[PDB]
Length: 103
Image (cartoon, rainbow, N blue to C red):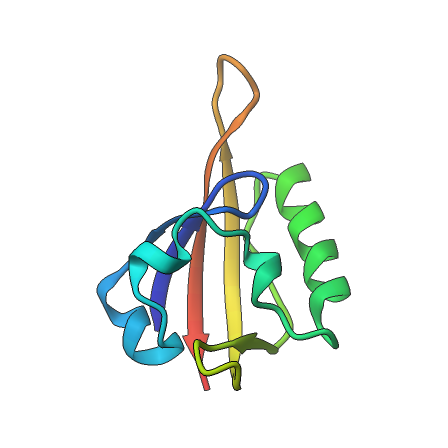
């Protein structure tokens, strides 16, 4: 229900308008941070494996429904569709598009 874009490492590069109402973070506090900073302890291992497969195959990867820590340090449930785009000259990832559905 909100879109974010990340580096190959998971660092937030962009968040759209709709996210602050959901996760409570303003853009300037979340941009530059890794998305490993917000994953619930119960889900970070499974989400890292999804991040691995995203960096390896040029295909959509849908995560499990995971918990994302909001600004008040409570959690919300998200399911994200991830896809990385590699630069054809350096093989580096320009960004990973993240479509985050909220529950």
